[PDB]
Structure formats: structure tokens, C-alpha cells
């Protein structure tokens, strides 16, 4: 059991293990498109003294954090141990090697989407975004008098084939991702893959349509088996006008009973309707997980709430360093210190605070985050909050 | 169709309409217990020129708001129009009379639980608390090393018959309600009713048991039909130690597959487990609705986040007044002004901000709340936040 | 295996066999109420050379047929063979004895409700009424502008406890039953039983309520398990105004999603709504079965459509006689003849024609009814039609 | 928002709107086959000042009405408003233009199949045929001794590939459609489309088979997911012998549990079985909707029951004219008059009477049809009845 970077000859073995580990696997032709996002030493395989029994890699990503600040981000992905090689510390060995490489390459954070919710905490990954599914029973939905864009004259929203308005979608998404914490740069090859899955497959998914606003779009398709359900795969709006306009159009799908979307806890949609209850939360789950690789770099890089006044504390991350943390005018200075710690937490907890989706108060109540001063707890809660709500870009 | 206060002779007609309007109706014997909470002119009936075709009333309640401040609260309840008398403006007439009386009596707020989510917005009621159902698959649940009270020696939690530890339950709840926004004083007659429903009914609910900590308790029962599901009817914990200890005991119900609880969005339970995903959100809904009766009284009465610095604005409530609002050192002065408004909202929106469960940002995005300054929006978000998360006491 | 009339000592054995044969069995106390409707030689038992292994009986009923004509009707009921004594010709022996007795007593027809739909055809019983279940999704239901009783002023319909308006229910039902083919006289002891089942049972059915119009009523209850479904057990309306008024009240049960009713194919309810499709047919089944005991007596007793002009034919019933049938001015003369038959059918088929629920055309297409003249077929179709649609009174 | 006849350049925009409005849409290649049935000014589009946001059209159809009389019929179809352009009166504008054109072209009736049951009443369309789904549990089904074609010697019914017996299917259907009210001429291009859908699709429907009698056929296929269910897509029989023979063959599909068919209320199948209950009604819905364009032309064109004697009345259609209606010897003369009206109804109601599927009595009970003489009501019921039961040809 040797741990190496793959050679050209290893990739057939890697695509076999992928096909057997992931039910959603998109085949080797399209794996080669995502493979353009893997840098030269971004991948490790385990061979059995010989076929591939383990693999892991990272993609080069750009993640927007609070303050509209963009971080080079190592996107962990394609992680699989053969079912013949479980309980052998293969994941621990592969994750340790990729973390060494990601850290030495100068990435301040790593990120992933978890197959199960109990694997990645022990490697310093913390859930950092929250997925909300809203199912609207659109037959009862009426917009509130206060809702934008419900007047006379022509609608600003168009029904279009996605594949004929690539540039407009790209330009809107680019604006959205630079502006929203959790935003990822979507490279050309992922726009290739998104629009390939927009077309109907024989005995697969149905044709995807788009609703296009100057400042927003929604891609949607009728569900395979439930023909009265429309699944919004993606809705990016840069302005409230665009969000409302697009949802007026979705509520206008008169042959559907229900519209479903994976969105975020702070989606305003419920407040657009006379009956907020018509936007039911059907499903909730962790989205993006963050491992903070360099604590001072990550803490210094993001913006903090201007509302909370200047304050200083000593943060200890477990086997991750101790820092004099000073926050004021929405910036942080984070410096080495050996002063007594006032707040302690494992690396994963910091991940979960970092994009503003979890409150330090909530993690303190669970004793994931220890302090004896509850004034500092209120101050952390306020400081680490994002004025713009954290959202989830795309799964990788 | 006359609108009067009921006389002794009207109450049979009112209990008939109740039996036909509410499936959960607990019968006349026990309606007489809740009736002790209705003050002398707290009820209106509509007679048909004659039987009761409409009724509404309010109970005298005490509601904890941010800053551990307790408000006299008119609890709207027992609202019903006969199915023979729909679309007759009977609800509008009854709600208008009770609002006159509640306002003239000197109640700063009114509150209710909604049968549907689209009735009460137009009367100035806004959803002010959020119910989260968590279903734990307790077979996979392991507590995190960081979780409190997982050491050697005896457990501090006891399994008990609820009916033999009334005083301890009362004393813990009393501590909980004074300390948590959304807290209600539970009077003796509701403790009578809670413990009556704790016993097994023939072809009804199963025996309720209690888990009792010095600083917390949980009442739970196995579900009627799903014999592998335990339903936590109520869990009140004053300290994190008590919350964790009680959940260790619930995860210890080894004959159950699943533990379900109606709790709040900031419940730390997920963070107590190695796999946060094991506490799935099965259900979300509006809890307590608030109508702010007197805007200056309510705004002045509650505490504000000490983190945000002093600031002034002009708030207009639609057909509800305009005020110079000044917030600093966690207090507010709210005075009459005719200065140009900087922030406008309907009365219901203020209800939804008032306990901290909804962010002004989120309601602005839906245009339920209008301003042109986004600095003020951030400042409102921060000011109206509760350091202690808002919870839901009991349905009425 | 002897076939006798029961003695007082046989009735315990009969109530045991009833308890084991019928899941709906209402116990011996209430069996004694129905037993008042059994005449002195109306019952047969089979003993095993000794316990009761077979029973059958008939109740004295009054059945309204087309022309508002009321027939003494032998209501077959309480038919059961022990599971230990199947495939022994016990049903054939019991049915043959009761038919002898019913015929010699001077009953023109016998009637029953069938447990299965393939037992009773071979004994000359034909399905004579049709049960339609309509489920209304009442959340979408709006009454058509043309619908009666949708103006200003007070509703003529009252919500009441059934048990306090017995006389009004009795008087309306009495008007309904005299006026509608399929109508049965409901004796005092069945009004006793109907109102006993109107009250809530522990771990049984919920409280029944009534909607009372001067010319109509509806008894309804929320379903045991589906708390958003209201089950109309019975709706008797003498005038269209009453039918519409009562359905406006049912659509007004705002806490229900769905209203369900067992009614008849010609129920006007769909035509009262802007969307006829909202009254979905969830279920259809045979109601009352008729065996014509005396062909000339039954054919002469009922009224015929005045529209079709005078005509004569020769009807043969298989092992039931041949008759010169002459119909004109809505009356029939039916006399013995040996003239060549023009129309042949088994006794059961005549049962199915007799109340107007099945068309001779439809039974001819299946060759249940043979003729060579299709002019006569059109003439039978028209003659045997009821101007008032055939309905189902109550199960026995 | 301009309302024009489409040009060649509009049809891509129309096929896009079709793909997004109809889940069953059969793609542009096959839309071009149906397009042969659209006459030169049979289509209208709405452009947004520019893409297609609305469309409607009519196909040239031939509809058999009572008396085996065939009417030129404008078949409304391909009606869609963009979800971006709802609540804009676009359907009202398009329906008004097509009605002008259909009326000026000299069509006596228009017809459609409704997506929802509450859209088309207000445009004068009334439900005119009824769809019954029968599901037979064929494991219990035995044919009655009276059923045709159950003797010795060879079966007259053959199992065949549909695609090899096109001419026989065409010739039987042509006989069926000329003979049955609701019958439509099926043109060559719809026979092309029917047989294309007869073949197995990858991850779609299974191979269709045919049962072929000299005077009848059935096309059937096993259901995609329920492999014990056979779905009869279509069964056309000209003689009772053919109907019975074909159903003996269907009951002979020994590897199926259940046979399902969309048929009509008067299908004799139940009466072919010893247990009529084995043919359960699983589903009921409106089929063909009729708008009577010219009242005197339509009323004069169809045959009336010869049974009812000559009579005269004055019919008023709401904003549709008043007529002296005289019916005798199965013909009607319908002439302009200003004499006082004896019977009033909206245009849609006449639609529903016209093919005999709804009784004037039933529509009177709902007050959709007003008269003060109930003798005339009985006379209308009888006159407008079809001796041959009304059936549904094919959806368009
Ligand atoms: C070598 C190259 C590296 C990454 C990679 C491929 S295919 C490919 N497909 C996807 S799409 C599904 C994402 C959801 N995912 C599913 C399981 C749970 C986590 C979230 N993503 C990639 N990163 C790659 C090959
Ligand atoms: C006169 C007296 C006034 C209030 C009152 C009774 S019984 C009684 N039972 C209850 S328990 C169910 C609460 C849930 N509720 C159910 C429907 C939706 C709203 C929330 N509550 C009361 N306030 C009273 C009679
Ligand atoms: C001796 C006396 C004779 C008839 C009789 C009893 S209980 C009693 N309960 C009923 S209620 C259920 C009717 C539905 N029925 C259920 C099975 C299928 C047929 C339809 N009816 C009776 N005739 C009697 C005892
Ligand atoms: C231009 C041409 C006009 C009519 C037309 C096409 S495709 C095409 N497909 C069909 S098949 C489905 C009928 C069911 N229908 C489905 C929705 C509800 C109503 C009933 N029918 C057409 N008339 C056309 C294009």
C-alpha cells in the first residue's frame, strides 16, 4: 500500500473506483473536463503493492468570503476508498498528504461537499453553508401588495432555451459570485457541463428551460416522475427586483402544483407571499465545509461587521496555534502570542464560524467553543456575521 | 348580526362552534380551566338576529421579550366563524372590536398562533417565532468529545412519572420563561391541563414520562402508531449542561429508532453529535405571531444589542404613526415626529422584527420594509437581534 | 344439518356467528333494536345435527319506486354461513326457504346490500342503485354565479348537535323517502341507532355535527385519522335550494381540505361549482339489489315515463313466466300469455331495470337481455327511466 | 402586445412555448404532422412588442353527433400563455379572435380537451363527454353464461403487431366514428403518430400489441413500472360480439393482475362478468368540451329521440339569441322569436346537453338551466338523449 501522485496509467483505475463509489458519476469523457481544474500535484492514489484502491484530489477554486474578498481555495473532491480496503487508515493517509500539499502550496482554506456528515469533522472541516429546500404550492401563492414588479406594462423576464443565452447566464453568475459569501468562480468547462445536462436524456431528465432577467436567471425542469413538480436547479439574482420577477414567472407555471428549490435560510421568497407558510421547508443539510489551513491568513483576509466596536481577545485553535485577535473598523489583525487563551475551539469550528452561517453563541452552548466571558461571545457573534447572507454556489 | 360580549347563556353555543371549528378541542370541562385566563370583557360573540355564528377572545398572558423584559400580552384565541357565515366580514368585525378593547385596556402587544399562515397579516400580526422539528436517528448518534457531562460517576438525570414532580417542573419552567424571549408565564390551570394529558388515554396517546435534571426536564411519549418514534412534547433547560444531559438520556432510549422535537432554529443539539446531519430538520413553521398595539411602548420596553453604537432614524408604521427612533446602550427612545421617514413598514413587519427571529435585511429584500440607506438596515439587523435565541413557549 | 326458524335459545349462537362474519357488527344490545324489524317467521338457522352454522332473515321495509309508489319489501340481511361449513349449499338452502316465505307472505320484491358483487345474481337479485363517492377539494371550490342562495342577508342553514333536532331530521327524511326511488321508511329504532353513532366513541369515531335547513340536512364528522377530511354520512334535501345551501355550508368548513360523500350518479354538486372537476369521483359500487318476487305485481305497481307513447311487447323472465306487457300514460298492464316472446332476460336483470339505474340498451349490449327489435329496446330504455334520479337510502 | 396570425419565423418560438407549457409535448418533427390539420388562418400568436408569449389555434375536425350526423368542428388546441405573461387577458384576447374566425368560417361548433376544468366554461365551452376508467382484477373475472362468443371452435380474435394491420384498424375505426356520437375522423397523419407510439422507446413505454376482430380491435401495453397492469390505450368495437370477444382475449392476459381502460359510463363490460364489481371505476373526468357557435344550426343538425312526441318551447341562450324550438319525429326546427322565454341557459350548458351525456334535469337542479315547467324539463331530457351512448374519440 504505497501513496503516490497518479501517472497517466492510473486514471482508468481511478475512473473505475469513481464509477463504483459515486452513483452520480458522469462518465470518463466528462471527468476529463473537471480534470482541467486539478493542478499538477493535486491528486494522490493508493495502489495495492497493481490496481487503485484509494484516491483523493483538490481542484483550484476561488471562494468569496464576507467583505466580497476572494480566496484561493483547495476544493477537496473525488475522495474514494475501495470497499475491499475499508478500516485501513487510507482516507487518513490520503487526507494528510493532500493537506501537507495544499498548505505548502499557500492555500489559506480548503473546502468540500460531504457524502456523509460525520467523516470530515475530525480532519478540521466544519459545515460553513446551509442548504434549505423550499417547496411552494404555487396554486395558493399570491404576491403581497409590497412585492416588487407587479404593475402594468410588459414583464422584464423571458422564457428561453438555456443553450442560446450562455453569455448572459455567465455574466449574471460572475456578478452574483463576486458579491455573495460562498460564491465560487465557475470556469468555462463547468458551463460546458451545466448546459449539457440542460437537454433531455432518453429515459433520464426532461428538457431544462430558463427564465432570464437583465439581473438574474432561473434554470428549471419538470421532475422525471412527479409531472406536477418543477425543480429549480439554480436561481442567481443580483437585485431584489430580479429575485421577485423570476419568482412571479415560476409561480406562473400554471401546469405545475409545486415549485422546489435548494436555497439558503435567509431566502426572502416566503416574505414575497401573502401566506409565508406556502414556502414550506421540505429539507435542510450542510452545504460547503471549510478547513482553515492558515488561521492568521484566513482571519485577516475576510471583512467583519462594522457595527461592533474595536475589541481584542486570545483565540486558541486546538493543535492549530494561539493568536492575539484584534477586530475593529471591519478588519482583523491576528498575531502569534503565548498570552493565556480567552476562547478555545477545534479547527473545524472556526470553519463553521468563518462564512457567518453559524453563531459562536450556538457553538458555545454545545461546548464546541469554550470561553468564560459571554460579552466576548456576543462580540464574536456580531463580528463574524455577514451583512450579505451566505449562500451555496455549486456542488463539487 | 349583532356583536356583543357573551352572557352565561352564550357559552353552550360557543363550545358547540368550538367543537365544530377545532379538531383538537379538549371538551367543555377543560375549556372552563382555560376560561379563567379570559378577563371580564375579553370575549365577543356574533349571534344571528338566536345561535352563536362567530366568537373571538383574548387571554391575559405575560411574554418575555429581549432584555428579559416581561410584557402584558393579549393572547388572541378561540377565534371561529360558523361555516354557514363565511365571507361576511365577521372575523374583520370581531378582530376590530377586540383590538379596540386590547388597546384601550393598555396592552402594548397582542399575540396568537395561526390556523393558516395567510389570515392574520392583514390585521397587523407578523410571525415572530420559528418552530423547527428535529428528528434524531438515535441508533447512529454519538456525542462529540467536546459535549458536556459525558464522564464517569452517576448521571444527574432521573426518569420519573411527570405527575409526582410538578413543583420541580414548574420551578424550572418559571426560570426558563423569565430568561428566554417568547417565554410565557404558564398559570396553575395550564399545569393542571399539561399533567392530565401526561396519562395514557384508551385508544388515545400513550403514558408520558419525564427526564428530570436540577436545571432542566423533558416530557416525552412513544407515538400512537410509530412505536419506534419518541415525541418530546417539551424540553426546558436553563443551562447547557442540562440540555446535553437530557439529550444523552433521550439518545439512551435504546428501544426507539427516532426522537422528534419541536424546537427553534438555534437549538445546539446538532453540534452535540459527531454527525450534525443526524438531527434532520423534518418541519418548519411560524410559531407565535405578534401585533404591536402601541409602537413607542413596545420599542421602548425591549432591550437592544449593546454591540451596535448609538444611532437615530425616523420609522413610519403604515396607519400606525411616525417616530424618531434613537437606540444606544441597548435602550430605545421612540418619540412622535413629522420629520421625513427613513424606514417604512406595515405593523405586521414590526411584529416579525420585534423578538429577533427575522432580520430587517431579509424583510427589505422582499420590500416588506423600505429604506434607501443600507447602513441603517445593517444597524437595525444588529440592534433588534437577541443575544439569547427566541423560542416558542406553548400554543394557545 | 336441519333448516328451522330460530327459537329464543338460538339467538346467542346467531349473535356469535354475526360477530365472526361481520366486522361492522354493532353488538347484541343494538342487534335487538334491528330485531324489532324482523317479522315472526322472517328468520331461518341451520344447526349442526348443536350450534348455529348458518342463518338468514328478512326485515319488513317500505321501498319507494318510480311514480312515488311505495312497495312492501322483504329486506334480506344477517346472512352468514360458518367458515367451518362453506361449499355445503347452506346459502342456497336458506335463500330458497326465505324466498318461499317472502313470496307466500305477498311481498312483490326483495332487496339486499351485497358483501361481494358475485354471490346474489344467481338467486335473481340485480344491482338496482349505484353509489358514487364525490371528494371535493373545498380549498379551490367557488360556486357558479347561477348557483342558488348566494346573496346578501342571513344564511338559512344552522350548525347544530344532531341529538337536539331529531324531529326535524325525521320530518325531512320522511319527505325525502316518499319522493325518491330507492327511498326506505326509516323506523324509530334506526333513528335511535343513527343518533347513538352521532356521539364520539373512545378511540372510535369523532363527534358528528349537523347542518339543518328547513328542507334538508347533512350529518358529517371529521375522519378518525385524516383530520383534513370531512365525511358526510348522510345528506337529505327535498329542494335544490336546500341541496345548494347545505353544500355552501360544507365548502365553508375552512379547517378541512376535502369533503367526501356517498351520493348517486346524478348528484348536481359538480354543476354548482365553476370547476366541475373539483367534485372527483373517488369510488363507485352497487347499492341496493332487487329480486322481483312477482313480475306482474312489480311491473304494474311502478310508474313509467309519460314521454314514450303506448306500446305492447311479450316479456319472458327465465323460469319466472311470460307476459303481454302493455305500457301507456305512464301505467303498465302485465298479463299471462303464451304468445312468442319478443324480449327475454333472467329475473336479476329485471331487478336492475326496475328503479331506472340501468338502461335496457346497456344490458342488451352484454346479452343479459335478448330481443331482435332495437325499436322496442329504445322504448324500454325510455319507459323504465325515472324522471327523479334513483338514490340509495341506508344500508341494511 | 400585438395579436397576429403566425408567419414561418414564429413557429420556433411557438414550439419553445409548447415544450414549456405541455409535459406531453411530442417534439417539433411530430408537431409538423398535426400542423397539417391547422387551416391557413387557424392560429394566433401574441408577441411582446420580439418572442411569442401567447398562442392558440384550431384544427379542422369532423364530429359525429346524435343521428349519425357529422359536423365540421373547430378543434381548439395548442393554447398557451407564457408564465411571464399570466393575468394579462391574453387567453381572453386569443379565444375572442379564434371564435370570431371560427364563426365567420361557418363552423357550427368548436371543441377542446381542457388542461384544468375551470378555464373554458366562461368562453361558452361545456363538458359534453365523460371518461370512465375501469380497472378489471382479471384473476377473479369469469364471463356470465349470457355473454356472447364463449363456445367451442376457434377464437375470431388474433394477437398481432399493430404496425402490420394499419388498414384493418383504419377501416374499423372509420365504421366506429361514423356510428358513435363523439366520433372524430382520424386523418392519415394521426394514424402515423398512433403507430409510432406503438413501438417500445428506450426508458419510455413498452411495445404495444393489438387484439384484432373483423368488427373491432384493442391496442394495449404493459405499464412502465407496474408490470402486472395492462393499459388498453384504445378499444373500438362496431358490434357487441366484437366487444365481448376482445374482452375475453384481454381477461386471457394471464401474466397480468389488472386491465385498465378509459371508456364511457355506459360500457357494458361490467354486465359481461358474473361479478359486475370486478370492473371498478378508478377515475372519472370531463372528455370533449363543446362550444355551440351557431345555436339554430347545431340544434337543427342533430337527431332527437323518436320516443318523445312533438312539442314546442322558447329557448334563450345568454348573449346567444332566443329561439322558438319545435321537436318532433326526431328532427328540430329552431327559428328566431321574441316570444317570452320558457327555458334559459348559458351557451356552455347547451354544449353539455348537445351530445346527450348530461340530463337537462341535472343541470336544472344546479340552476345552470332555468324553466318554471318541469313537464318541459322531462321532454328536454328525453329529446336530447342519444339511443347510442356518447363516447370520446381521441384527445387533441
Ligand atoms: C479528476 C476529476 C476530479 C473531480 C471530478 C471528476 S468528475 C466530477 N464530477 C463532479 S459532479 C458531483 C458533485 C457532487 N458531489 C457528489 C458526491 C458528494 C459530494 C458532491 N464533481 C467533481 N468534483 C468531479 C474527475
Ligand atoms: C374560553 C376558553 C378560551 C381559550 C381556550 C378554550 S379551550 C382551549 N384550548 C386550547 S389548546 C390548543 C391550542 C392550539 N391551538 C389550536 C389551533 C391553532 C392555534 C393553536 N387553547 C385555548 N386558547 C383554549 C376556552
Ligand atoms: C336480528 C337483526 C337482523 C338484522 C340486523 C341485526 S344487527 C344489524 N346491523 C346492521 S348495520 C350494517 C349494514 C351493512 N351491511 C354490512 C355488510 C354488508 C351489507 C350491509 N344491519 C342489519 N340489517 C342488522 C340483527
Ligand atoms: C401546430 C400543431 C397544432 C396542434 C398540436 C401540435 S402537437 C400536438 N400534440 C397533440 S397530443 C396531446 C393531446 C392532449 N392534450 C394534452 C393537454 C390537455 C389537452 C389534451 N395534440 C395536438 N392538438 C397537437 C402542433
Image (cartoon, coloured by chain):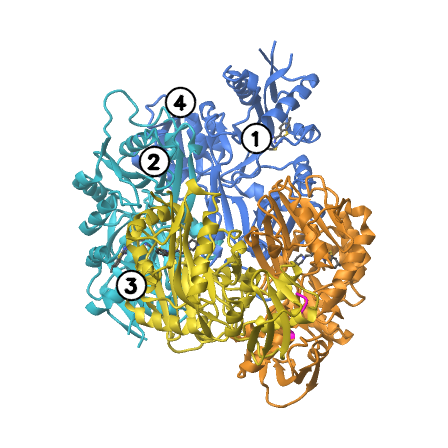
Chain colours: A blue, B cyan, C yellow, D orange
Q: In the image, residue D130 lies at what x, y percent? A: 62, 62
Q: In the image, is residue D385 part of the stretch drawn in magenta?
A: yes
**Do tags 2 and 4 sit on the same chain?**
yes
Q: In the image, residue D389 lies at what x, y percent? A: 66, 65
Residue assigned mark 3: B16
Which label's residue is closer to the chain start, 1 or 4? 1
Please identify the quarter of the rendering in which residue B230 is found. Answer: top left
Label 1 chain ID: A
Q: In the image, residue C35 lies at what x, y percent? A: 33, 58
In this picture, which residue range is highlighted in magenta?
A: D384-389
From where the camera sits, is residue B128 visible? yes
The quarter of the picture where the C terminus of chain D appears is: bottom right
Which label's residue is closer to the chain start, 2 or 4? 4
Residue assigned mark 2: A377
Q: Nearer the viewer, mark 4 or mark 3?
A: 3
Q: In the image, residue A56 lies at what x, y percent? A: 58, 22
Disc 3 from disc 2: Cα separation: 53 Å
Label 3 chain ID: B
Amino acid at each position: 500500500v504505497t501513496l503516490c501522485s497518479p501517472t497517466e496509467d492510473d486514471w482508468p483505475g481511478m475512473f473505475l473506483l469513481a464509477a463504483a463509489s459515486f452513483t452520480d458519476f458522469i462518465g470518463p469523457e466528462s471527468a476529463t473536463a473537471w480534470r482541467t481544474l486539478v493542478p499538477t500535484d493535486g491528486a494522490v492514489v493508493v495502489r495495492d503493492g497493481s490496481e487503485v484502491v484509494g484516491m483523493a484530489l483538490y481542484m483550484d477554486l476561488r471562494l468569496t468570503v464576507p467583505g466580497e474578498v476572494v480566496l484561493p481555495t483547495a476544493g477537496l473532491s473525488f475522495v474514494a476508498v475501495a470497499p475491499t480496503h475499508r478500516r485501513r487508515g487510507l482516507l487518513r493517509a490520503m487526507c494528510a498528504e493532500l493537506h501537507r500539499r495544499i498548505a505548502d502550496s499557500g492555500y489559506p482554506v480548503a473546502a468540500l461537499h460531504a457524502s456523509e456528515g460525520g467523516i470530515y469533522g475530525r480532519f478540521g472541516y466544519g459545515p460553513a453553508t446551509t442548504l434549505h429546500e423550499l417547496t411552494v404550492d404555487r396554486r395558493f401563492a399570491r404576491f403581497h401588495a409590497d412585492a416588487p414588479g407587479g404593475g402594468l406594462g410588459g414583464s422584464s423576464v423571458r422564457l428561453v432555451r438555456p443553450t442560446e443565452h450562455r453569455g448572459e447566464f455567465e455574466a449574471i453568475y460572475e456578478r452574483w459570485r463576486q458579491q455573495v459569501p460562498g460564491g465560487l468562480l465557475r470556469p468555462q468547462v463547468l458551463w460546458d457541463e451545466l448546459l449539457a445536462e440542460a437537454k433531455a436524456a432518453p429515459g433520464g431528465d426532461r428538457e431544462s428551460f430558463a427564465l432570464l432577467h437583465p439581473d438574474g436567471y432561473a434554470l428549471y425542469r419538470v421532475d422525471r416522475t412527479d409531472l406536477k413538480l418543477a425543480r429549480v436547479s439554480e436561481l442567481r439574482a443580483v437585485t431584489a427586483d430580479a429575485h421577485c420577477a423570476l419568482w412571479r414567472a415560476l409561480i406562473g407555471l400554471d401546469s405545475m402544483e409545486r415549485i422546489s428549490i435548494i436555497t439558503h435560510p435567509q431566502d426572502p421568497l416566503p416574505h414575497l407571499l401573502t401566506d409565508t407558510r406556502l414556502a414550506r421547508t421540505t429539507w435542510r443539510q450542510d452545504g460547503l465545509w471549510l478547513r482553515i489551513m492558515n488561521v492568521p491568513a484566513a482571519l485577516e483576509a475576510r471583512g467583519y461587521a462594522h457595527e461592533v466596536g474595536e475589541f481584542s481577545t486570545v483565540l486558541e485553535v486546538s493543535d492549530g496555534g494561539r493568536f492575539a485577535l484584534k477586530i475593529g473598523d471591519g478588519r482583523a489583525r491576528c498575531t502569534p502570542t503565548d498570552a493565556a487563551a480567552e476562547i478555545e475551539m477545534d479547527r473545524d469550528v472556526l470553519g463553521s464560524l468563518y462564512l457567518g452561517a453559524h453563531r459562536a453563541s450556538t457553538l458555545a452552548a454545545a461546548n464546541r467553543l469554550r470561553t468564560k466571558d459571554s460579552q466576548l461571545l456576543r462580540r464574536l457573534d456580531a463580528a463574524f456575521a455577514s451583512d450579505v447572507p451566505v449562500q451555496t454556489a455549486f456542488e463539487f
